[PDB]
Amino acid sequence: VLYVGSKTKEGVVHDVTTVAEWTKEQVTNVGGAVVTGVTAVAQKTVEGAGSIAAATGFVKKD
Amino acid sequence: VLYVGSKTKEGVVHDVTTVAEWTKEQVTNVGGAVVTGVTAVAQKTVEGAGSIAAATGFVKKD
Amino acid sequence: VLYVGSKTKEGVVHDVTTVAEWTKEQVTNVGGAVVTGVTAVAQKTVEGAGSIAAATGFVKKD
Amino acid sequence: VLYVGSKTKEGVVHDVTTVAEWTKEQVTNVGGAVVTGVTAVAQKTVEGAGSIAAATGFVKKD
Amino acid sequence: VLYVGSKTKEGVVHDVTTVAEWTKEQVTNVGGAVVTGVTAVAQKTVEGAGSIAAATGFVKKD
Amino acid sequence: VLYVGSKTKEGVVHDVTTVAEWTKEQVTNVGGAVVTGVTAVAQKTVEGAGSIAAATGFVKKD
């Protein structure tokens, strides 16, 4: 293995653009997740049993 | 392995752009997560059983 | 392994841009997480059982 | 005339993005203009006879 | 005329982004202009006869 | 005229970003202008006959 002037992009997130304008937003909740923003998870490796990698809006009610 | 003038980007997040303008936002809650912003997790390695890597808006009610 | 004029970016977050303008935001809460800002976690390694790496908006009610 | 939370953009230039990569470029010249970069003129008012407002790559050989 | 929380942008230039990477560039010249960079002129008013406002790469050989 | 919490930007230049990386650049010249950098002129008023406001890479060989 050998490079020159190279580039590598394993596991990234880029150029996420959100624009809200005149936004009215009621939200109620009782006991459960609610998500409204912009989530950005970026991982390279995840290992192991029973794992939960990069959850968003989760409820685990065993 | 050997490089020259190189670049590597394992596990990153970049150029996240949020724009809110005239935003009205009520939020109530009882006992459960609520997320509205902009989350940015960036990990390289995660190992081990039972793990929960990079959760956002989570409820674990065993 | 040997480099020249090189660059490595394992596990980073950069160029997060938030813009709020005329933002009205009520928030109530009872007993549960609420998140509204901009979170920026950046880790290289995480190991071990039962771990919870980089949580944001979490509730663990065993 | 009266505003609120307003915005005006008379005569601007913004978000000019140039990207060159592995560019070989010979250029000769004798006695005449040559332009290769990125020009950005932004004017509001220009008045008067015979004027030459915002020239780029000009030759006036009277 | 009267404002509140306002903004005005008469005659500006902003967010000019240039990126060169592995650029080889020969240039010869004899007696005439040559331009290669990034020019940024930003004027509000220019008046008067015979004027030459914001020239770039000009030759006036009367 | 009267403001509150206001902003005015007559005649500006801002956020000019240049990035060169591994740049080889020969340049010869005889008797004529040559420009390679990043010029940033920002004027409010210019008046008068025969004027030359904000020239860059000019040759006036009368």
Image (cartoon, coloured by chain):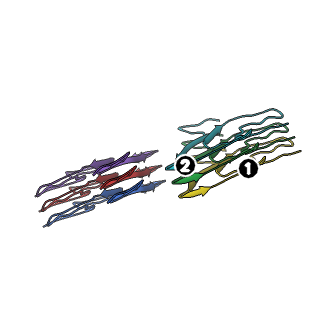
Chain colours: A yellow, B green, C cyan, D blue, E red, F purple
Above or below residue A26? Residue F19 is: above
Image quadrant occupied by the N terminus of chain B: top right
Residue A52 figure quarter: top right
- Toward the top, the furthest residue is C48
User: Is label 1 in a helix, a strand or a loop?
Assistant: loop
- Amino acid at dot 2: Lys
Could you say where residue A9 lies in the image, as x and y percent from the top left? Answer: 63, 48
Is residue F27 toward the left or the right of residue A41 in the image? Answer: left
Quadrant in the picture for the C terminus of chain B: top right
User: Which chain is mark 2 on?
Assistant: C
Dividing the picture into quarters, in which one does residue D36 lie? bottom left
Residue A29 shows which numbered tag? Answer: 1
For label 2, the crowd category at 10 Å Cα-Cα, with few meaning under 14, some 14 to 19 and many 20 or more, is few
Circle on res. C24: 2
- The front one of F48 and A29 is A29
| Residue under the point 28% across and 55% down | E34
Number of numbered markers: 2
Question: On the rendered structure, is D33 left or right of B61?
Answer: left
In the rendered image, residue D17, in percent from the top left (x then y), is placed at 44, 55
A53 left or right of F42? right
- Whether residue A27 is visible, yes or no, is yes
* Residue A61 percent coordinates (x, y): 86, 45
Marks 1 and 2: CB-CB under 8 Å? Answer: no
